[PDB]
Amino acid sequence: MRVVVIGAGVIGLSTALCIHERYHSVLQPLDVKVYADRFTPFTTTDVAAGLWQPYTSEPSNPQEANWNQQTFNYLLSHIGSPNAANMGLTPVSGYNLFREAVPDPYWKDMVLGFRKLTPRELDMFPDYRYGWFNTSLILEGRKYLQWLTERLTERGVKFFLRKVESFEEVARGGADVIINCTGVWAGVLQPDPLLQPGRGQIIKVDAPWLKNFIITHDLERGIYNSPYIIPGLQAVTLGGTFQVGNWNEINNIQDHNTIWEGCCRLEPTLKDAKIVGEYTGFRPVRPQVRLEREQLRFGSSNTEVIHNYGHGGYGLTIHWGCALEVAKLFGKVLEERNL
Amino acid sequence: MRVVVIGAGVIGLSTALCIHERYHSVLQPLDVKVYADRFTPFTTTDVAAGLWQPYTSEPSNPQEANWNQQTFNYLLSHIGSPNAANMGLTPVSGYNLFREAVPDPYWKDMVLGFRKLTPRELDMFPDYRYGWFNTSLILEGRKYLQWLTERLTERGVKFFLRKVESFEEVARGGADVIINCTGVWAGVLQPDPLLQPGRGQIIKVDAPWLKNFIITHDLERGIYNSPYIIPGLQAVTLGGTFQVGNWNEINNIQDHNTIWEGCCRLEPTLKDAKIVGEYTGFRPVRPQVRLEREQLRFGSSNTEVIHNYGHGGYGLTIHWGCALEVAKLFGKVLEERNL
Ligand SMILES: Cc1cc2nc3c(=O)[nH]c(=O)nc-3n(C[C@H](O)[C@H](O)[C@H](O)COP(=O)(O)OP(=O)(O)OC[C@H]3O[C@@H](n4cnc5c(N)ncnc54)[C@H](O)[C@@H]3O)c2cc1C
Ligand SMILES: Cc1cc2nc3c(=O)[nH]c(=O)nc-3n(C[C@H](O)[C@H](O)[C@H](O)COP(=O)(O)OP(=O)(O)OC[C@H]3O[C@@H](n4cnc5c(N)ncnc54)[C@H](O)[C@@H]3O)c2cc1C
Ligand SMILES: N=C(Cc1c[nH]c2ccccc12)C(=O)O
Ligand SMILES: N=C(Cc1c[nH]c2ccccc12)C(=O)O
Ligand SMILES: N[C@H](Cc1c[nH]c2ccccc12)C(=O)O
């Protein structure tokens, strides 16, 4: 059948692939196309630091932790393959610093080697007073996008640089099912006051001697302003902002300065990191991820729509779960058609 | 008094500095010079991977462990300073893989976060079956040499490219006290059948996505013969050879191939690492480090000599301890002179 994936960010691409991988033998003509107004390096995904780490507290939608876990495993499993880095993946170990004692993350056991930092360790960071240590993964957006793309491409999924106007339009196109993976911009296709830009700017700097991530946490200053540093495949991400509702898409000087000053403070060696770029992107914020089926009817047209958006600042971290999920629904959609 | 340090590797330089740092104030006319036939990038030190980690086997002498510990601390203490990386220092976390259960290292508590790997972790490198995980430091030779050098230089220590032919000789120059830090070549100045070249060749490769060290152990094949990988400040060290008695100083193709093949197995992603260089060096092997005073008399000449050599494959790892030690003796030498 006719399937159209709207979006070419981590979400759509995975999902496209995932659906395609799982039902191309179960269905001869299984046409997949991907429509997107932006492709890497242009998506939000392309800006993401890429570290796998959910949020401190358990998700309102309890199922989401499983998605996080499944993602971590699919990733871990590729650790050992000669392709992992080509896939934009590698293990990274690091610190979560806090200014006071804090309960253990629900994912404490999903990552490798979770443990509370000792005082000697804490002295490596004179500001913080409590924290954790653990090993995890880095799944770099831009790279993963390129991989997913090559994979899809070989599987014959076709891409089109298009701005979808209305689901109707697509549907009118011929779409049988439509997978909505439009991230923060999902609103335009259908309003959702729940969804919102969680803006973040970051500085990319060249500072190879930094081998571990350090993610600082402020307790009376929202989730993002604290400075954070995340070593990636080829550069380091200096970070520190999460402004909900800001739609400004240009990097701002003060943000640049606060990020720079904050990190330089947490890691004085940055005093010599060469800055290689700055970026800003919109985390698709929503209280809970929207991943559900929805029948849209336009006259005589019976087109199904599966939503998968609102992954906030953890899209990479949870991408695979949701993908598996959409697949399951896409299956039911297929089952209702008796295949 | 006139003091002459023979050697400009990690050992001499530290020692020079260290002595100078403590008695420049106290000792009246204090004149330190460093004589060496090789300077970075030419020393053995310049080839060292730079990871702090003593041998897995217990200390040969007691002092060796304290020296190791003192070194680790002096290093840790600079973690937080904005100079550390300029000093060639940074934390690095990593794995020690074994093919069977093995007792815990005596340094288990000197490093940060020592812990036994879990099975999931073990899965990352299938061939092994047991191992550890811990965080430590990297003190890169070439860089540390340059730092020590600048420091010494500012303190006014003078350097001379020269080949000492006999302690006597140098004694003749009016040298008051000589510090022998000639590494494997210490023999020539005075025979020591205990000392021997522990040859090691390594490939430097560009593979930034590798953030942690992995040090394999073949228990039958000896120490540092198994493949090992150690991410450094700007490149990665592929390693794997420790041939005692080999004085060949040219990189050998076979070695290059076994190193390359071994690491490529342990870490398949290396398939795409660009090789940036190969190097070979002589670990100054000796059953116990030689660090002791020795009066050499030549006619009417009463010149003291303090030896500090034979640090094997753990020179960086233990440099500071020994330095502090030589200092203490140099002090006694000064005390016997009533200052
Ligand atoms: C600064 C920052 C750091 C981050 N770091 C991390 C991290 O370390 N770990 C982690 O897991 N997550 C992180 N994230 C979150 C991650 O970036 C997002 O969760 C993820 O990128 C969301 O993916 P997406 O495909 O849903 O959105 P995007 O990647 O933005 O995908 C949007 C896609 O839909 C298209 N599109 C939308 N509407 C239409 C339309 N009407 N017609 C056509 N095409 C349309 C766009 O062209 C694009 O193809 C970070 C995000 C930011 C901003
Ligand atoms: C392949 C390899 C990997 C290593 N990795 C590590 C590691 O990861 N961690 C660690 O702690 N250690 C490591 N080591 C060990 C470390 O390299 C040595 O322990 C350390 O370099 C010894 O320092 P040194 O100054 O005593 O010898 P060198 O660095 O070789 O110093 C020799 C100096 O004395 C001079 N000299 C000698 N004789 C004379 C003379 N007659 N006249 C004038 N000058 C003279 C030479 O020019 C030079 O100045 C490694 C070594 C090798 C070979
Ligand atoms: N996910 C990241 C990195 C990050 C900063 N603070 C965090 C707290 C919990 C989990 C992740 C993070 C981002 O910049 O969006
Ligand atoms: N010191 C190193 C690295 C190394 C390889 N095997 C080891 C066992 C114990 C301690 C260190 C190592 C060197 O290459 O000399
Ligand atoms: N080299 C001789 C004597 C001398 C002067 N300064 C030092 C320092 C270290 C050893 C010897 C010397 C000279 O300068 O006449």
Image: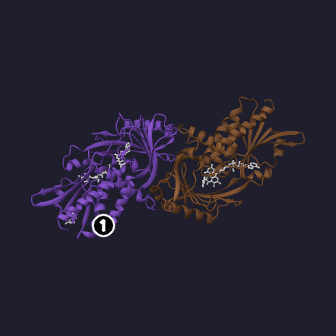
Chain colours: A brown, B purple
The quarter of the picture where the N terminus of chain B appears is: bottom left
For residue A281, side relative to residue B199 (left or right) = right
Amino acid at pointer 1 = Gly
| Residue at horizontal 45 percent and vertical 35 percent from the top | B129
Name the residue beneath numbered marker 1.
B156
Task: Return the x and y of residue B47 as percentages of the image width and height.
Answer: 36, 48
Residue B42 in view in this figure? no
Dot 1 falls on a residue whose secondary structure is loop
Q: Could you say where residue B323 lies in the image, as x and y percent from the top left? A: 29, 57
- Is residue A77 positioned above or below B329 on the image? above
Quadrant assignment, res B324: bottom left
Quadrant for the C terminus of chain B, please: bottom left
Q: Measured from the top left, where is residue B110 in percent x and y?
A: 39, 51
- Image position of B121 (left or right of B196): right
Q: Alpha-carbon neighbours of circle 1 within 10 Å: few (<14), some, or many (≥20)?
A: few
Q: Quadrant of ligand 3?
A: bottom right
Looking at the image, which residue sits at the far right?
A299
Residue that lies at the very extreme toward the left in this rendered image: B299
Closer-to-camera residue (A246/B69): B69
In the picture provided, is B101 more to the left or to the right than A282? Answer: left
The number of numbered discs placed on residues in the rendered structure image is: 1
Q: Chain under label 1?
A: B
The image quarter in which residue B89 lies: bottom left
Mark 1 C-beta closer than 8 Å to ligand 5: no
Nearer to us in this view, A23 or B327? B327
Quarter where residue A13 is shown: top right
Q: Is residue B27 above or below residue A146?
A: below
Q: Say left or right for A290 vs A223.
A: right
Residue A243: where, in percent of width, then height? 67, 60
**Residue B215 visible in this rendered orientation of the protein:** yes
